[PDB]
Length: 319
Length: 319
Ligand SMILES: C[C@H](Cc1nc(=O)c2cnn(-c3ccccc3Cl)c2[nH]1)C(F)(F)F
Ligand SMILES: C[C@H](Cc1nc(=O)c2cnn(-c3ccccc3Cl)c2[nH]1)C(F)(F)F
Ligand SMILES: [Mg+2]
Ligand SMILES: [Mg+2]
Ligand SMILES: [Zn+2]
Ligand SMILES: [Zn+2]
Image (cartoon, rainbow over the protein chains, first blue to last red):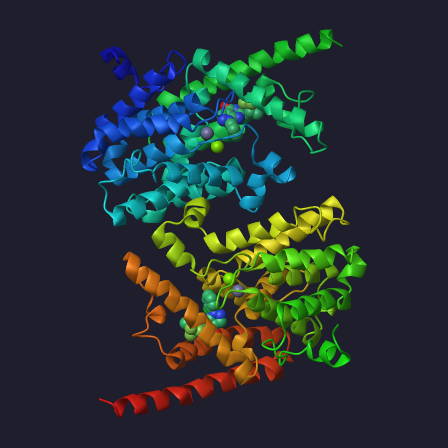
């Protein structure tokens, strides 16, 4: 069960995603669907809802970073944004359903090695998706194979036309998570910002791509205590890759290279050239987002810069 | 064993594809690869190249239209164009290898039901490819599945950098055969066309995309009875899809409805609004195309228009 305290904190981006076990996370995800009025407006069989969440969980891999806790993390942040930015006043329920469901399924069956590995290693994935966002494509397919089994199909009671609309929206959002397209997408969105139109369908599609992108890389928005472990879990996975990459001939990226990257320098670059700019333009649309999320981001940047001095200082010694 | 008479008619769009058998065509294909000096300039092992073309032939299905012969026509037409338009003076042997390989592989393992059926019926392909060019994506995938085996890999003797550029090219061409992108591709082309530039890598990519598109739907460019049978084979496959759709209760395209489609009306629109316009544009770059390909297309159009009059009169005589 969840205490009214937990259920209360579940709305803030300060929620401690580490305090829980799969079962307790499944319950929170479940709470979110009810509380958002999704179970209600889509006639989601409450039993199916919980069975779906179990099948989703079952399909996430036990990786150091790209795992079910990450999934929950992204979904929970998305949930926070819905209340923080009062999204239910700008988005239809079908839009919210898409944001939430896409967030929960965006990394289904992730293997721990990104697209670059897949393509360079000429993997069965990279071959099947002709080197086009192979991971993202795969997550999305698994997401719909799951929804294909009537028992997990939380969309049973939605008419075919509504299903089509929801499916197309989820695919757009999940593929939009591939960071390779980060600049392209930010340009498109900033271009629409010059005069945003909440009634312009294309304007909203980009805003939704931006929102799920925000949640998927929002770790640094959370409290320093909650955020740090994630950076280490990602680098574990990244090293796991660059290890296998160098011992296979396949090239390696600087940010995944032991001899080149450091938690601090990395996060200073990520926070300044990715996270703060992105959340900056989003603030022009949502002012409350500046205090609640752009603040910890600045703080986080500042802190990793102070940690950079000490890191460099220790480096001098081991030389 | 091709005679010298054959090796000569094989460079023209008047070649009768309906004569030869799988065995013989496989020879013509093999010939084309040597004749174009792809073996030479790339170091293709003449034995591997012969196995590969067999690996390929096996992977095509026994469909009335989308079968190994269609494959043959597309590559044979592509071959005719390399000679007619002297493409070896404009394109590198790399691009020529891409164009020919792409043409041969473009419909690998086609099931006989188009993307609309896949999408509407929510097939594995549709689910797997997220409704995005599911058939074409699958073809290009089965293509590289074959080049994956060490025994069919006709690219084995190519540096890493080389294989990359080839693969990307092939993915681009095969994915460009999806008619759903016709208007989009024709536009990008007609644009670059306002000031073509055989130097501009993007100008050339669009030309290669337009070249394979021409070859994929170029049946009407051939002689009246080499062409006519093809229209029949396509409808046999189409009616095969609509019968199954009606049965399964899925929507039916008009041009696949026995009570609506007539060869006459069909080929009139297709020739006037799809074929002729595309070749006219290509003729701006290669004037010699007008006499060898536009000519038969204009005759095809007129013939079909005359054929529709007959059909109107004939039917009026019955009501
Ligand atoms: C090199 C990474 C930088 C980085 N910082 C994050 O906070 C963060 C959040 N998500 N991702 C991420 C994860 C997977 C793929 C792409 C990204 Cl972007 C991140 N990557 C790190 F130093 F290890 F942190
Ligand atoms: C309804 C079709 C129209 C048509 N005419 C062709 O000559 C032609 C050549 N290729 N394709 C074709 C085949 C498969 C998919 C798309 C196209 Cl475009 C054709 N489609 C037919 F009148 F029945 F023929
Ligand atoms: Mg991902
Ligand atoms: Mg095709
Ligand atoms: Zn993710
Ligand atoms: Zn074809």
